[PDB]
Length: 6
Length: 423
Ligand SMILES: [Ca+2]
Ligand SMILES: [Ca+2]
Ligand SMILES: [Ca+2]
Ligand SMILES: [Ca+2]
Ligand SMILES: [Ca+2]
Ligand SMILES: [Ca+2]
Image (tube, rainbow over all chains, first blue to last red; front, side):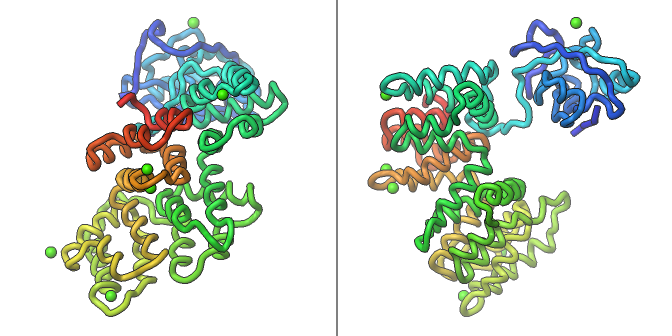
């Protein structure tokens, strides 16, 4: 579950 | 296992190039994947009003192939976000996207997303089949049963943008019988289909308590949260309010409590002491005493997590001479009994629960097409493979076989496609 806003 | 490759000459779908200028809040999209060394990076969502959305080229599930003329196939998640964050405000970025690899799909469904999806081409071929003299139902079945439910949402959008008429409207006028009942159900979002099937079961004082129990006792927390919202947008009244209207007694309390969707989420630590205490409290409320303490049954069976209650029902056999299902068949009766029986079956083994309901809808004379169609439509993208697996183990023959012998025509071909396989 890696998850990052760009 | 999801397919992975570092060479672009091995990708399946079509490719899209984009140029996004960095705003004060970034490019306006989020990325998933990237822990597993061989795992794609895919767009999870797009911030509306953001750069990625207002350009209209990027879509969710897009595999990021290359960033600024540099192939990022196999890049770690942290290596990619550092490329996007190094770009200053006002500068742009070149994104090569690959469309055709899917995302948060269910490993156990039977209807998967079409890879070479073309919503315009699909809405084109459907109109040609609808307008064909002697409506061509073969093509309509060949398309709609071979698309994911969200792909069918895009086809409905494209069909209305070309013919200026709704896809559900044109298909309802062109189809008839049970085939219409299946196709119209496939065009609804899972919340809309459940919300409509629930209202349909509360049509009058003669409530279809069977269909009401099936939908309520099988849907999870997140599924029921969406159902309650969609049910009010469509009918301007709370799902709970209609349940209170068309139910009464303890059966009302059990249906209202389950419909709230506030079951305790699955815990990470197993509460062995609560498993025993819940098991004793179920035994003290039922078999051990004269009568039944129904509220204590409703509280335990609706509030504890599903992995917890499975262990509670196994521990319950240590205290009671009859297991949980047999205890229900003698402590309560009527619609309340049918509710507890279905609820416990959905907790112990939910795929087996739907396998029995499919067998029941076909074993006797005729067909319970209402139950058969709803289970095939609703479970096609959730656990249909597990439903087929439990069915063949218990009943010898496959679910495909029982649908083949009980249904005919294009209505049969539609159900067999939702079942999957050639058997
Ligand atoms: Ca390039
Ligand atoms: Ca025809
Ligand atoms: Ca009793
Ligand atoms: Ca024992
Ligand atoms: Ca039958
Ligand atoms: Ca039957």
